[PDB]
Length: 160
Length: 123
Length: 100
Picture 1 (tube, rainbow over the protein chains, first blue to last red):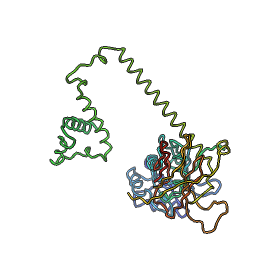
Picture 2 (cartoon, chains in turn green, cyan, blue):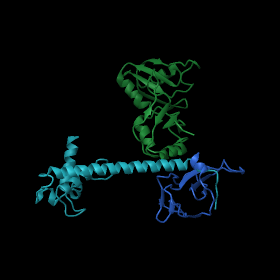
Picture 3 (cartoon, one colour):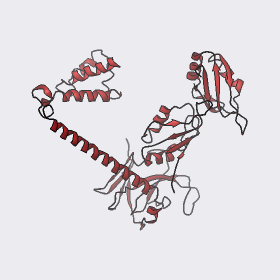
């Protein structure tokens, strides 16, 4: 897990030897793994590249971070408001700093991860201090231009 | 982080003995080729340096132990218990004020989510 | 549902005064005798009672419980912020509402 780098944000043009060919300049990528879905039978955008040394994986994570690969925000990492279609290049501290401009955050946010890879699932949950920050996130942040990924902010629970 | 904290404590001790706002022992040190990034207010350590300077100024008070001796806080446990009870009452009043502010914010959020947003009038 | 049905609507005439600042509108409202502050919100012109053509702008509307909502159209994309807790104020002593 230390020598392997988890890549997120892969489109349909990216393939299993294509990621190994793109990561060959960063370091000696020994193997590439792409988990296939059960309903569609294709990649879900997240994969893994197992290299030989941990320094090559660190250089690939520091070089290929927030890159625009196949029209997709590909990024390598070390393997009541709901935000969907978020970029995997952002972290919890980056999401807390991005959410601090609209309103005040009550605590540190959390992002959902896949049970197989564990880098990024695609959705996240963040809680605001009051309902005014949630309304400002649903008015402004729900549709704002993020890092090559259109996010969507919505209410997790609402009572009619 | 011990050397930076010691430098901040030395700057707070040297700046508290000044007779003016700008005529201090640290303003002339900035022009004497001494790098001090904690003097600018843009850094996060400046908020702690200001609190250290405030504590150094409060350590120079006449009831702080320079020319007088405290008798109520040092020789009366009942006065300390009354001060602790007053601090607990102030904390309870602050918690009640925060709960009232949260209730007012919830009432404003309930009133804003129930008003009609289709009756537009441009005058 | 209970607060929306019990809200009285007589629709009085509001008094708004705009001023181009550089670094802000002042709405004169009567005494409401309540703790509910008037709230401002920016919406689109796609939803209307009659749906007129060529509606592709935004409108910032301020609304209160005893008074009617006053709306101002903004042709620009983003020149200010329509947040309530950021750049708005409501003095209950003089009953003056300001938003910048």
